Image: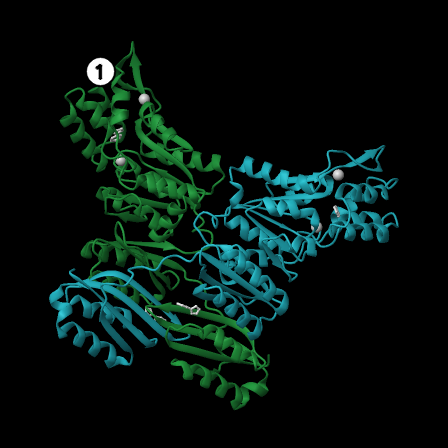
Chain colours: A green, B cyan
């Protein structure tokens, strides 16, 4: 172990190259400092930093043994005294997810040039999904203080090209996420429950219009919920179970929750909706925490009011904190997914706030935006790949 | 998107290749199915599966545009209608850690040939540490039912070549480990506390001899603890604090625990030793769970007995289970690290049982064995790299 030598083997993948190389090196006094190898589309690259006696490195036996063995079977090898080279690359600082249906070449090219223009190095690119959407990951090394610019640059690329682009800190701490909360309406569940209750009153049109104004930040949430629930005054309480049994999970929601249990996440829901509807489901979904509002009932009939206190925008953040404290999870390790301005405060306080098919008020504040109608695209933003989900699911 | 074409770019890394390629492809009707890229020791490989109109794929414009752009600046590119190729590789089944000081070429070559002989494909090799030991990772794809043979083959390589070799399941579930327990004596802490107590009685020689016989499985643990603690009959109870203040953490133990808190592990200790000594420390180390034995004291003096019930070999497993149930962690997601036959049952029940500088009885039963005097080599077996630990620590 006097001097360091770098051996690099490239060419068309073949059986036995890795084994052949280290057997040859063992006829010389070689100890390993670092080995990197990958095969991409049958192209092999094998990089080996070793140290050996200055005697062997300075003489032609090591080189002739390596070169003859590698060249004989079809590949190429270079050999060079390094001494100055890094031993082992540093970790990426950040990771970038690109989700599209499709992802065009132009979309990806724009990301790559956006990245380059900021002096960001691409350390790795891989696929993470081929269904329900194409998903691609770039691990990168961002110059210090450039990552605000990078998110800004990539959000434009995202809108201009019709791909989701999420930039996420790739450090040990920030990526040990352990706790996720979903908004219910238009996030975990298709549609808006309060609209399904109002349909029982022939008020769906009015309620839906107030809901869209509320979910765009156009109306104060508390006022908007009182106006909407009022249209329910007089309906019998039986209507709750009825709507409860009508609900449909967002597509990919079961996969999302099941996969997140495999990873040991605490899972909960924070809703402006109604505990009597969400609890039946949270229990069916084996959740750990429910926060919701409560409908007032008199003589088995809805009064058109809710029983305070009301979970408003600020209250959803407050439930997240409460959930994180009870679970023993620092807030930087929490995930919130929602769709409306109702969720702005909850996404800001979460470690990672995901806007799922969201109104512009939310998209503008989220750490990340998803634009396709599959809730399991959340799994890709949490470092999970399609193939891994299918492996786990197939093993049962 | 009628047909699938595979573009593969290889050569010496340069600025702009990724960006150049996708800009060229955007002048044709190209959508992305999969992108893999890495640079190893300045050798770039970029593999791109796309789909485009059968018109563009069948004509020479796409090829001449790609070939001219890539060749102009120094690299090579191939282009081929695929249609039959996989879109996105499957995940590895297992991962192999090779720790050595040093790792010789012969050691690594033996691993590579052992792997090959069982029909195991190496999907990736990377470095995970350059200090305190050289650490290398191979992600592999093991034929179903071959992994018992693989562990067997690699354990021989390990002893024959003086490297630790750990084979670990690389599935989503089994690698979301969330809970670790350490044995104390000769694991988290240097030396054997009961030997430090006996030194106060001039009994160290006898106690140490009984301890080594007990830690090799030669003696029943319960009998061996009674004989040893008896030599303490008559010492004043003050001797506990004294030894407490003398203790030295295993080297790298602070890094191990700190890094494991960053990842959100529940951390505890299970010891045959004495709660009055371990508690002062567990609290100093911010642990979540302590299990230990209790020294009997009369009139401020040790009687030479322990206050049952005694944590024996079976009792350490029982505390692990108890700890896992209280924390909400399935046993397949738990980690136990120990050194003596005292820990055999605890390592068997844990998801991953690590033998740290252990007696042969333990090594023979552990999922993994570490042979170097740094407890932070545990972090490498849990998927953490040296560079990541240093990044996190530098960020404070
Ligand atoms: C050094 C500089 C740039 C790159 C690179 C980034 N994207 C493709 N190659 C890789 C290493
Ligand atoms: C804002 C908009 C809709 C809702 C809701 C719909 N169903 C239950 N709550 C709650 C707040
Ligand atoms: C297919 C077959 C073998 C390999 C390989 C394993 N180790 C080095 N190359 C890679 C792909
Ligand atoms: C077996 C051997 C030693 C010990 C021990 C040493 N110090 C505290 N307990 C416990 C069991
Ligand atoms: Cl309710
Ligand atoms: Cl005690
Ligand atoms: Mg909603
Ligand atoms: Mg011990």
Q: Nearer the viewer, residue A11 or B196?
A: A11
Residue where numbered disc 1 is placed: A235
Q: Where, by quadrant of the figure, is residue A208 drawn?
A: top left
Residue B130 point in image, percent of width and height: 54, 67
* In this view, B176 is above or below A118: above
Say left or right for B15 vs A89: left
Q: Nearer the viewer, residue B93 or B46?
A: B93
At x 27%, y 27%, the residue is A222
* In this view, A166 is above or below A21: above
Q: Report the quarter where the N terminus of chain B lies.
A: bottom left
Q: What's the chain of the residue with tag 1?
A: A
At x 12%, y 72%, the residue is B59
Residue A87 point in image, percent of width and height: 50, 72
Crowd around label 1: few <14 · some 14–19 · many ≥20 (10 Å): some
Say left or right for A118 vs A90: left
* The residue at label 1 has a CB less than 8 Å from ligand 5: no
């Amino acid at each position: 172990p006097k001097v360091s030598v770098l051996i690099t083997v490239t060419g068309v993948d073949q059986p036995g190259v890795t084994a052949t190389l280290f057997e040859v090196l063992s006829r010389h006094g070689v100890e390993l400092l670092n080995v990197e190898q990958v095969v991409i589309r049958h192209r092999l690259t094998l990089g080996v930093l070793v140290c050996c006696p200055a005697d062997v490195a300075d003489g032609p036996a090591l080189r002739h043994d390596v070169e003859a063995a590698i060249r004989k079977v079809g590949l190429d090898v270079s050999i060079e005294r390094s001494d100055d080279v890094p031993i082992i690359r540093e970790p990426s600082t950040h990771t970038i997810f690109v989700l599209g249906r499709p992802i065009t070449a132009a979309a990806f090219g724009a990301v790559a040039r956006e990245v380059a223009a900021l002096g960001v190095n691409i350390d790795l690119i891989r696929g993470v999904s081929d269904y329900p959407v194409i998903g691609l990951e770039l691990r990168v090394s961002v110059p210090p203080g450039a990552d605000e610019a990078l998110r800004t640059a990539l959000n434009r690329v995202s809108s201009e090209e019709h791909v989701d682009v999420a930039v996420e800190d790739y450090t040990l701490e920030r990526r040990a996420k352990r706790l996720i909360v979903f908004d219910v309406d238009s996030t975990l569940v298709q549609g808006e429950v309060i609209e399904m209750l109002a349909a029982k009153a022939g008020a769906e049109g009015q309620v839906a219009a107030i809901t869209d104004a509320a979910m765009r930040g156009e109306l104060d949430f508390a006022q908007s919920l009182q106006q909407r629930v009022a249209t329910l005054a007089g309906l019998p309480a039986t209507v709750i179970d009825e709507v409860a049994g009508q609900l449909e999970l967002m597509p990919g929601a079961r996969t999302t929750l099941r996969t997140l249990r495999r990873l040991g996440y605490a899972c909960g829901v924070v809703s402006g909706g109604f505990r009597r509807i969400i609890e039946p489901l949270a229990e069916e979904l084996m959740l750990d925490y429910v926060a919701a509002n409560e409908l007032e009932i008199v003589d088995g009939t809805l009064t058109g009011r809710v029983v305070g206190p009301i979970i408003d925008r600020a209250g959803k953040a407050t439930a997240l904190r409460e959930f994180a404290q009870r679970a023993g999870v620092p807030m930087a390790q929490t995930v919130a997914v929602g769709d409306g301005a109702n969720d702005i405060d909850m996404l800001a306080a979460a470690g990672l706030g995901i806007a799922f098919n969201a109104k512009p008020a939310l998209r503008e504040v989220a750490d990340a935006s998803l634009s396709h109608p599959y809730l399991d695209t959340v799994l890709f933003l949490l470092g999970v790949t399609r193939g891994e989900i299918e492996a786990a699911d197939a093993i049962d």
